[PDB]
Image (cartoon, rainbow, N blue to C red; front, top):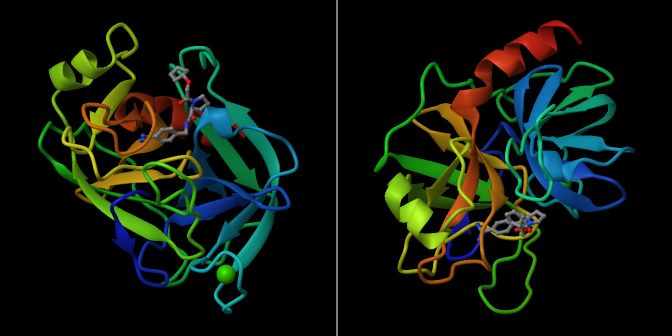
Amino acid sequence: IVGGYTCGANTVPYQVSLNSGYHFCGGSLINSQWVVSAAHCYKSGIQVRLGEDNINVVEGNEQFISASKSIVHPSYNSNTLNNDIMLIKLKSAASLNSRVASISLPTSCASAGTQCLISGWGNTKSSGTSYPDVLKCLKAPILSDSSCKSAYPGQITSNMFCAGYLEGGKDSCQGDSGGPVVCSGKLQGIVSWGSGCAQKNKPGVYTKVCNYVSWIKQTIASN
Ligand SMILES: N=C(N)c1ccc(CNC(=O)[C@@H]2CCCN2C(=O)COC2CCCC2)cc1
Ligand SMILES: [Ca+2]
């Protein structure tokens, strides 16, 4: 997260870290057994880390749970990142509490101009590399699709939306991938892609979760 702030410990209780010997992506807990992340975060050998703030220190509210299965969207295209969404099932049910909590799926899409919260342990530098150990947050509005498509001609599908600031300075980045975009208490997006980070006229691009609620509900009910 570039241009953001330290969230504070467990103030984003649906935020997970995906670990394969190291943090490699974020995710969102959607019930005690399931996580939503980006398809480009797929790998096997995933451990889901819940209750995290500093991901390099055990502070005592963590739950580490191995994944039993992963399910990449059937229509995920890795060349264009269309349908960049994946579901991860926990081998054992998480213990929900104030610091480990699920986030609700949208009952509808969100509108342009709506303010959202984006969070993650990714790079905090626009040019260069600096990884935080504690969770970073950013408030950012949904941008118009036109502004979105203008920045990325020919690359935006109906399954994507932009959020951030066209002026630059504030954005998600590498390592925030798969993490939540929460608007009005609903999971409306997943950190997916962008050109660089926090660049002028290159806002972040997010998976449009409201398009997948049926697929998510049907997939977890059958798996
Ligand atoms: N500025 C941002 N908000 C931002 C945030 C996160 C990321 C991490 N994502 C990535 O790096 C994704 C995953 C693999 C290819 N990738 C890419 O960004 C570059 O690939 C092309 C982008 C659209 C079609 C493929 C990149 C950018
Ligand atoms: Ca920790």
